[PDB]
Amino acid sequence: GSAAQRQGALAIMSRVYVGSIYYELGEDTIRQAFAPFGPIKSIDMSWDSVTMKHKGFAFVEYEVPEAAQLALEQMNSVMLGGRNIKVGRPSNIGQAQPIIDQLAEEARAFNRIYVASVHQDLSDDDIKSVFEAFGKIKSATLARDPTTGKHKGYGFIEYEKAQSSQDAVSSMNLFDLGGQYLRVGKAVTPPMPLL
Amino acid sequence: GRGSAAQRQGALAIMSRVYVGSIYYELGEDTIRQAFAPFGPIKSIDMSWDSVTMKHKGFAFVEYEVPEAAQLALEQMNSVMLGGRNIKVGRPSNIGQAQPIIDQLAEEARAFNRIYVASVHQDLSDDDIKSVFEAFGKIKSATLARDPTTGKHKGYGFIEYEKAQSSQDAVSSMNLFDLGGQYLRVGKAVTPPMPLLT
Ligand SMILES: [Cl-]
Image 1 (cartoon, rainbow over the protein chains, first blue to last red):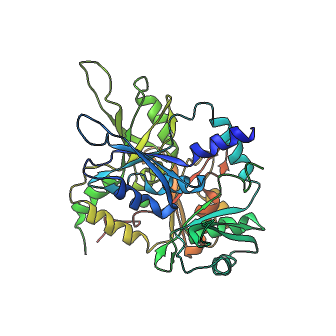
Image 2 (cartoon, each protein chain N blue to C red):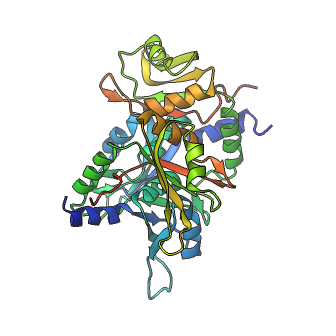
Image 3 (cartoon, each protein chain N blue to C red):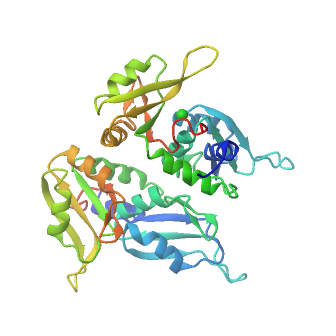
């Protein structure tokens, strides 16, 4: 995978198909429902010019593949506006699948977990202390706004041992911290995929 | 106290079925069965039928013998690509007032450290499964469901642990564990052991 191919895959991996959206629901409802797994980068909502409304589906785009993966595993069939929404991976890809597979394989070489819904008051050291209860930590870093320096509600933690990362995901996904429920999952891409 | 025997039974039945949509026109009952059987033996499948075009309407309802199988299928078969399309899996939209009983059952289930195990190779026995799983902690019981006529196990069972951490460790370590040639499908129970008893 050339740096360009890998980047193309990462973008596809960051989006999820969302279908069976109740006609009365809009972008804001969707955003609110999918934001817990990472901050939404954008949403492409279907739209019909004659009827003046969406076609019942949308593509939610996240800043990282791990957020889309968690949303995929936790938002499927959730009831919104009286309907059980459907969540899936984009059907397009077109030949991006082998790169995606390669990234998933490369990710297994790291004991990295993705953490979302991290309360604003928590700091890197705070998250680190909490999570090092499951094992020794190589690094714990919260993504930050390049301008402000405030964290964006999510981060990555790398453990020395696989058992530690497995124990952490199992114990911390949906763990109530600071008033919100953390959304935790195993990484689906290696740390510096384009290196 | 939520639900009499009849109400609970009605909920259990709904809990044992999953909606399967976006099925490629060329695919039929057999392909769906083969795709969903890993989570437990399929009891039946209600496939949509158009007739005028003599084709299914692209969706079906797979029914399992137990709610835990439908739960695992729901978590693992969603968006899987079949016939070139990413199938959709969800819970029946019907229910109609069954939701509160289902919630009650899920709550009662948490009082047990019970896990569901599917795709158990025929050669394994109860003591076999038990030894393997007791590596995660002390086991109260390990039982494989059986054909009432033959006595042969039906490829799935339940295991109760003395401690919750044990059951949690087991699900985490054994789901998708390659045993006897197939991959075990493991999950936490969604209903209490004898849901229909007093
Ligand atoms: Cl049972």
